[PDB]
Amino acid sequence: QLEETLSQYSGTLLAVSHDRYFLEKTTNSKLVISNNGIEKQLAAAAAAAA
Amino acid sequence: VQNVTKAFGERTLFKNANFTIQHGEKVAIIGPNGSGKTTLLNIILGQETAEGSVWVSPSANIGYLTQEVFDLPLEQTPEELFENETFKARGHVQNLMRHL
Amino acid sequence: KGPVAKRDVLPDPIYNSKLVSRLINKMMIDGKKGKSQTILYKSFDIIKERTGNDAMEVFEQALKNIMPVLEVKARRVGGANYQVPVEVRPERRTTLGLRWLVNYARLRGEKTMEERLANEILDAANNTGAAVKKREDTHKMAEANKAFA
Amino acid sequence: AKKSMIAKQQRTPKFKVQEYTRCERCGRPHSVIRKFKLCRICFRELAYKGQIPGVKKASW
RNA sequence: GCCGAGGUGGUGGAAUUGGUAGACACGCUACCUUGAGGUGGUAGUUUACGGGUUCAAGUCCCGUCCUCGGUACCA
RNA sequence: UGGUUGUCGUCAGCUCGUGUCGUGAGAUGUUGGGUUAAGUCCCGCAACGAGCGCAACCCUUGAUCUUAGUUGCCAGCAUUCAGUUGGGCACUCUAAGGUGACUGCCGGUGACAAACCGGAGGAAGGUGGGGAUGACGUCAAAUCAUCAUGCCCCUUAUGACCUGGGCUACACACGUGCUACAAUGGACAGAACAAAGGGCAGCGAAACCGCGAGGUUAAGCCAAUCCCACAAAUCUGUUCUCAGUUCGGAUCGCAGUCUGCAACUCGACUGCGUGAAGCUGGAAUCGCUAGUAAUCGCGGAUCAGCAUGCCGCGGUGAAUACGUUCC
RNA sequence: ACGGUCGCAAGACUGAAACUCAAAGGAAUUGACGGGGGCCCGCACAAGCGGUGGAGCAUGUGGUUUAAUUCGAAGCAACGCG
């Protein structure tokens, strides 16, 4: 139910979750922390779209 | 959060990581193991070597949830803990919210 | 009826490009080229400062990342709502790139559209960015509906 | 009430502010032009009938 | 009079004490669409009553009123 | 009912003469091929023509030649606080007469036509941009309240005067509009640029006073002179830093100003204080193809006074038109 | 419908009247319409830019209150209209 209602939540959420299936209801943009700081992703953003 | 840098002695996590998020959006923060996920929110929300600039809205009411359970006023009753003003503030606000 | 064509003005006093004046005519609110030229030159001076390059090459690189190859138009037959993928002719590639730069720059939100357009160019350069959401999503819509052409 | 009201305008009232503009050819206020001292429709009619020495059809 | 049953919104009606002028399907109202109706789309209105128990009551409890039916005087 | 309009619609249609075909209603022309913005024009045709429509002539803008120089203009000529003076009609300007763009000329396509596509010239290129112009008719559309009106009705009243109120009501809906929700922003200071139009019991300089709305005396002007009239967005500095705020101004209290017998219902404006809803809007829906949309001020009618409406005026000034699949 | 014949049945065949209307109908013409076809055109659609619908007020109109809220307009083509 927290997976459900946080989708109907009215924005400004910073959802750290080590799950892969919880964030499928609570994600529009991602912050992938990686080597040498953040990576502000808005999609998968892998393999450097060409 | 502009030009942020976070280091622990020689353990360096953040370096010049410029991102800016406004209201009304779902921000998922993913770290495989130790990406500072828990560390960023502390250095979003606090001082202590957020090297750079972290600006946040002064009139926003940030409700915070921790990973670690070590922020309880221990040995208190949830009666005294939860702010229950008059009559249905125990029931219609609170005790229904607990049992339900 | 038939196709009609248009024109645009060649130079800019700093950065002598056609397409930079095309962006000057874009993002003009209420008939004010002066505000858009000031915003534009302060933004390109930030792009020249913060990254030690000439902002022409960063700006064209960002364009190359945003310019979509494939629009997907509509073709409704019956009750079907089919979408048909269209090879975009490169004029519309440039103009959709400029619209997406301008729209998602002012849609970002920072403490001037100087900074917003500059950071949007800096994101579309290092391809992950806000207009490139629209690039990726249009290519995914053309990739899924490629059966019609 | 038409000729009575025309007659009342043709009077001198108690006060100068009771004075209002009126037709002089086809009795009505609301759009009597001060220059011609004429009602609007009567101005259109007479200006069609070749009178009123200034006005022709306008284009510019 | 006695026994048994139900008393909610304009309607029929679910709800094991935990939030309902109403949650569910209709009506109803304001708008949209249409030439104007209908369909369709958007938003909107204290539990028969009175007194408790309870942190909380449609519900648990004590009383009153109404209606269905069985059980009687009489034709 | 006359008269005068909306609408389809600036759509390209609508008819008639004479002829022929059909018992007749009708048909024909007006259909077909190309072409157009066009029933435009050509070609073919049982039709040949014609009329109302379309276009053109009319007004404006785009440029140049001539005339005409003050109140307009200042290039060289010196004086000027100042185009003020003398000087000059060159230049802009003004307002008259012209010239000018006609597919005219080239090449290509296409019946050889009509026309179309590119090219050259040119300020202007294919009705150059716009206006005015609104066919037969449709809605028994609108107007008996601008007027005139046939018929019917009232008449010491359904007519007339006067004051007062109302046409500004207010729980609600609904058209059009204005202002915002903000950093391309708000406030403050500096610099510049307009067009069009108005002025006789009117426009009203300048000076003075008032924070301001304005006030008192008054020059010039029946106006290319003088006034309205200090354009504003813009540009450049200072300042705030993303909040229901240095956003926005509703609403409201008090004290004022002007107009006018008189501003209570029921005027505009100013000053102080208060500062709301609103952080870009659901279904749906509208305008616009270029100096347009967006935006910024200016002007004039009406009128003593009342403009967010309307009618014109300039300022900056875009994005897009692949196409006709859909409404 | 009644009667009759045929039929296992369903029904077939034969077949009126009271009553009711001043039309029903055919073919063809001119139009209009089609959730018929073709061709074309218009900010009509698409391609865009800005809005309206949300808020505040100005303004006009419906309802309602009224002593009167004067009269006229009412889909496009009434509703900052006379």
Image: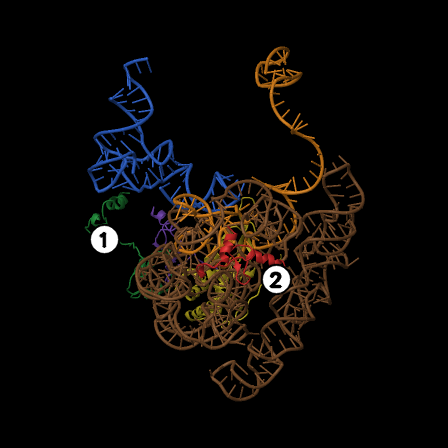
Chain colours: A purple, B green, C yellow, D red, E blue, F brown, G orange
Q: Relative to F71, is E19 on the left or the right?
A: left
Q: Which residue is mark 2?
A: D56
Is A7 in front, or is C114? C114
Tag 2: amino acid: Lys
Is F149 in front, or is B37? F149
Task: Report helix, strand or loop for mark 1.
Answer: loop
Residue F221 place in picture, x, y as percent: 52, 74
Tag 1: amino acid: Leu
Task: Report helix, strand or loop for mark 2.
Answer: loop
Q: Is residue C98 visible?
A: yes
Crowdedness near tag 2: few (<14), some (14–19) or many (≥20) residues, C-alpha within 10 Å: few
How much space separates mark 2 and mark 1, taking CA atoms? 91 Å
Q: Relative to F260, is F91 on the left or the right?
A: right
Q: Which residue is mark 1?
A: B72
Residue F225 place in picture, x, y as percent: 52, 76
Crowdedness near tag 1: few (<14), some (14–19) or many (≥20) residues, C-alpha within 10 Å: few
Q: Image point 44% across, 60% down: which residue?
A: D17
Pointer 2 indicates a residue of which chain? Answer: D
Task: Kindly check if marks 2 and 1 are in contact, taking CB atoms under 8 A apart as contact.
Answer: no
Viewer-side label of 2, 1: 2
Residue F226 place in picture, x, y as percent: 49, 75
The correct choice, above or below, for F86 with respect to F214 in the image is: below
